[PDB]
Length: 230
Image (tube, one colour):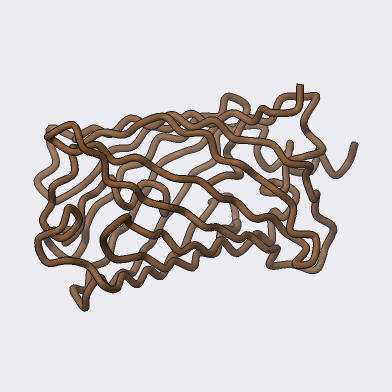
């Protein structure tokens, strides 16, 4: 299938990745740059993010979802349901509001597209309404990450998908900080895209530190696999 082969050719090997974020939470401005690689055949991403502005004013785990669904491994039986690769190389817009339970919210807009060989995720984040001494601004989140299933549906109206899901950030009293995600994706180009039947992506994420890195940073390893249509 030349449409499948096309994303299969853009993603059938290891693909360098760049991520650039400009953020403002409760007016605290910060920038982050990330680099790494993705191997869609295996659902694998490895990335290292650096805060280029000094200390990151929010917990690194609250940014994990914002910092590449085109790197999911879609099983061969499910290749018709891969919207994310179908939009490449021109790419897609990914927008979210993330509602933190009893606290503020992030609103993000990202463009995910190729720039030559490199797959770029360029993001603007605004955060509003955070409590000074809540779990976000107070840095009360553990540096770890649970596994989550993400439910994808078509938004045929908008020639894209809608994505909805709740992340649980563990807190160091056994509590969770809920982060309620509402997501919309739409293609950047005017070409054909795959509008999926409802399915999920299963995510696992591991957070770590580069023992040689003095800058505020996060090393992120994620495995992502599509399922949910036998």
